[PDB]
Amino acid sequence: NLYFQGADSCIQFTRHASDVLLNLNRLRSRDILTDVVIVVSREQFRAHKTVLMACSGLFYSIFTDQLKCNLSVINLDPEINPEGFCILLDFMYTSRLNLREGNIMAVMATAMYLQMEHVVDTCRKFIKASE
Amino acid sequence: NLYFQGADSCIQFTRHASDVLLNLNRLRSRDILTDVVIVVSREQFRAHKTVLMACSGLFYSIFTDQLKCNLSVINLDPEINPEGFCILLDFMYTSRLNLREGNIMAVMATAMYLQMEHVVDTCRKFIKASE
Ligand SMILES: Cc1cc(NCc2ccccc2F)n2ncnc2n1
Ligand SMILES: Cc1cc(NCc2ccccc2F)n2ncnc2n1
Image 1 (cartoon, rainbow over the protein chains, first blue to last red):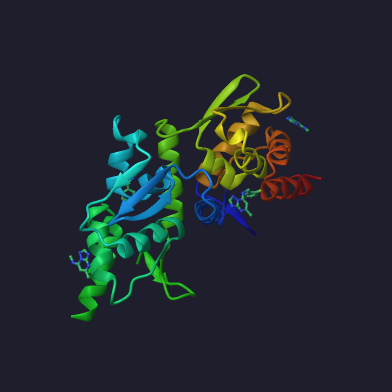
Image 2 (image 1 turned 135 degrees about the vertical axis):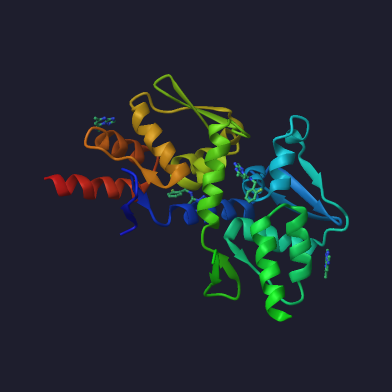
């Protein structure tokens, strides 16, 4: 079955959350209802503010700010590596984190800046395994 | 661990999709970045168009329409039961479907109208078990 008896009264659908995320990523790929452009070292990434806020403490802070919530363009710190940001943006929309020896430092520094502690801790654990 | 080696190269975060959905529901509860009001028999429900489109074929069709995508208010068919709609809206944001003997017919008819076939099939299976 696609469902089960949850701990509470309700039946719960096993694949619902992952199917929603897959569909949000399909909207992103098709540029449907994207409402922000994230600029990183002149690279541009179109996304949905709600997805960014649901994954990142920095984006949650920006988009809950009365002044900043209505910005259509957000420029990140020029020190931020676009590949590191791209890997984290894909992670937000897919649950898959493409960590490689060549990108782990950029991913970790970007996750720190974006306040994604779970990703930072994961990078730290992978780095610790190599030393 | 909060992660595993996916079938592909990437590490995957087990709870990421459900955590995103939980956070989207927290935004909904706080009325943060909600961009549409769904009106059902004069009852109003604030939501995020992207979440609605990711769950419902009717909302996908409406919000991908060049004319309708920019509507802030969507009126549903007056035949639609507000409780049935509320139960399905909560399901979209939580993966939990509060089916009860007293609401199953309204939920099924609403899921048919909203084009949520997985929910319709589930209602059909529960009804079949009672006969
Ligand atoms: C605790 C919480 C956090 C959060 N977003 C920011 C965020 C998400 C994931 C990981 C780290 C992080 F800082 N949101 N968004 C809506 N409601 C929330 N409640
Ligand atoms: C196949 C698909 C469907 C869909 N939304 C509509 C929808 C969602 C869940 C269940 C039924 C349904 F009709 N979206 N949304 C973005 N990309 C999509 N791709």
